[PDB]
Image: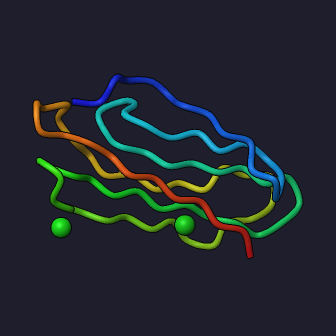
Amino acid sequence: WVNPGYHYQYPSEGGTWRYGFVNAGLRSEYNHPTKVHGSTVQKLIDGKVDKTNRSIDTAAGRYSNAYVGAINSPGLKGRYYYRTN
Ligand SMILES: [Cl-]
Ligand SMILES: [Cl-]
């Protein structure tokens, strides 16, 4: 199970990174105001990777969108990634 709602980090590279269990999925979303950027999320069940979703290379000023639809079940955990180009 994942304590729901976006969690936030502020990369040294710039921008805002938000991720977590939100609106029926695991999500990783990164906004960089000027650079091409992206994000990735992995869905874990009992520690095993069930799915990986990688955002496309995303335009400056928009949040990248990495998502896996999920039930917030007892075995659910997420792992989250961001990138700049
Ligand atoms: Cl990424
Ligand atoms: Cl695995």
Rendered residue at 74%/42% (across/down)? 10
- The extreme right residue here reads 34
Q: Is residue 72 left or right of residue 2?
A: left
Rendered residue at 55%/61% (across/down)? 39
Q: According to the image, what is the colour scheme of the structure? A: rainbow
Q: Is residue 75 left or right of residue 15?
A: left
Q: Is residue 45 left or right of residue 41?
A: left
Tell me the quadrant of the picture where the C terminus can be found.
Answer: bottom right
Residue 17, placed above or below residue 66:
above
Q: Nearer the viewer, residue 78 or 65?
A: 78
Q: Nearer the viewer, residue 61 or 51?
A: 51
Rendered residue at 65%/44% (across/down)? 17
Rendered residue at 23%/63% (across/down)? 51
- The extreme bottom residue here reads 85
Tell me the quadrant of the picture where the N terminus can be found.
Answer: top left
Q: Is residue 15 left or right of residue 54?
A: right
Q: In the rendering, at what x and y percent does residue 61 appear?
A: 80, 52
Q: In the rendering, at what x and y percent does residue 36 appear?
A: 76, 70
Quarter containing ligand 2? bottom left
Residue 47, placed above or below residue 59:
above
| Quarter of image, res 38 | bottom right
Q: In the rendering, at what x and y percent does residue 2 appear?
A: 29, 30
